[PDB]
Amino acid sequence: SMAMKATRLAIPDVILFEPRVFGDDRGFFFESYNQRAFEEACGHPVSFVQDNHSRSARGVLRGLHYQIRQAQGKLVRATLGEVFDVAVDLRRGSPTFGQWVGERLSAENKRQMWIPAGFAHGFVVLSEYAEFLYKTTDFWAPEHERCIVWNDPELKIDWPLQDAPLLSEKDRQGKAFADADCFP
Amino acid sequence: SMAMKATRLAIPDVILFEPRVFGDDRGFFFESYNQRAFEEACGHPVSFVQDNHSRSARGVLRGLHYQIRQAQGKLVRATLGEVFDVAVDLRRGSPTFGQWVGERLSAENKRQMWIPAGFAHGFVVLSEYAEFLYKTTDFWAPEHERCIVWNDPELKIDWPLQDAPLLSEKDRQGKAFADADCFP
Image (cartoon, chains in turn purple, yellow):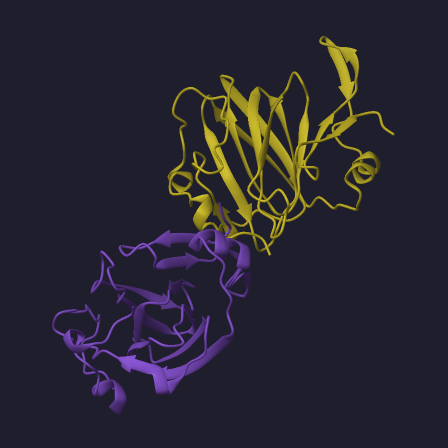
């Protein structure tokens, strides 16, 4: 069925993609996205309207973000460095509501995650510096972004970390999972 | 067009040659290679810089070899015994990427295969002993040879075998087609 690997995770709708590479470390070529494979993989059509690119230093943790209005699916990867990327299922009635999955994505391993509408998203940087890019199905609007605090006790996420995250004020002020409005 | 038969296989760039023989089993003469016929057959110039000769016993399977750097076309035959020789297309964008073809080459049938740059190559010995020789367009460098495991499930190669291959450690440690770096 492919020519990039696709693997459903503990939470099935969340998918990990692995591009096939051609060439080697001194020259290589790879497909970072293929509408056909991606749609066959996720089982439905998708339109990406915005691409976002960011750079953040070791230990920066941007996180537990999601928009309830102007909801968005996100396809994320690391073109530089290594992050641990996390997805939380906040879908009304989901059998896996309140569950999370996480994976290391890096420029070396070239892995990506699709995180559908209805999930909260986050990552922490593990390398000296990380460059993160994602494609979304709708635009990032601050007036609509909610947040769940990274270190929430019930989610009890396994941050491969071992040093306090450098968080933004906003993310520090994150809501407790218990108090979090979730997705219809 | 000839005076050795040339036949394109299911994967067109891979060619099977059959020399015309003169004489018989108690004396015979045949042309194992003719720059002119070969170039007309394969459609472009070729230079061969190294010839390799090997002897291996029944069931030895040396395989799924290719070099991405110092890439090589290979023209192979059996001067003694019988092998089943296999070619796998690993060319970025090839319509037949991930496809394979195989043929029995022997000292008796005198058949040969041209396996261009961009393919992985392998053979298993079917006779008591086999002597294998090939001409390549660039030199065998171990520091560059990659390998796909002979019994890969997706390639699902039809090894006329019926007994476990005696493999080298290296070939045992072969990569899965899925994880294999391929040719730009």
